[PDB]
Image (cartoon, rainbow over all chains, first blue to last red; front, side):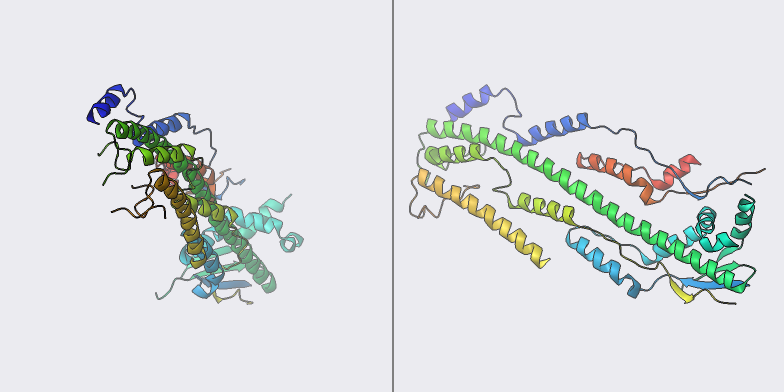
Length: 54
Length: 241
Length: 48
Length: 44
């Protein structure tokens, strides 16, 4: 068994293939890269009185 | 010719309606309140808004009867006052006009107008909080499902190698290793593997996921519909002087 | 909450059932008919 | 010939669009706020 385990491990190209946590960190980076904050409009105050005409 | 009202934060019995609605949402894992004192303070704040007063007078058919107009509105709006009055919080709201009956009708009318505005915004908040909960739980579920899929994919690869090692070690039948479990034996491992490759929906074997989906559906179905309430309690309703 | 817990419970059971189905297939594949004397699909009880 | 405005920190209802955006980000493990009072203080 050790012999075959060894040659399996030697053949591993991508540490992510056996590691779920790594695959998911990749997913996170992909989703973070795709995300946009696009122009949200808002007003940084509330009028108690809008500019008066005297 | 001055009408006055004394006003105090609302009592729990006036919140019963809202409390039923908060309970529907509490069950759905959304903990939401409209604080009785904050609602009151919001009412006071809006009452004190000159712009809101003006919009009220202009829209009031009553006031309209009795473009020099603008100066008139401005002069009327100067006669709405609110003052802080101790065992419990209370404010005196007053309006002064020529007729006594005019004073009372305007004050009462304005109070109702402001009151309707606070209930409108207040329920709008609850609705918005619901909208955010729904959006979040939905997007998180979609994400957790992809995360789960990725773990299954990785488990499949590991099970594949488990097969090879079991075979190499000549373990066909279940036995009577930290990285590639072998105990099940090649015969079992082979069927386990094909079962797992066949999995099409990560939620079929995972109760948690099925439940999170139920929660999303229930959140989507939920409504906050127009609850009526008063953001204050009258100690004195607008007087007829 | 009771109503809800019921449905949550049902969902749990349905998922358990699917797991047990697969347990049966793996039990059979590994030739375990009688109780033996696996973290995902328990087979110790045997196919019978 | 003097115009005046009275101005107060914004209320939650005006933040809803922002809070949709902060939620997309919250899911992606980024906890972000624009504090209503701080926004106001920056305006002033």
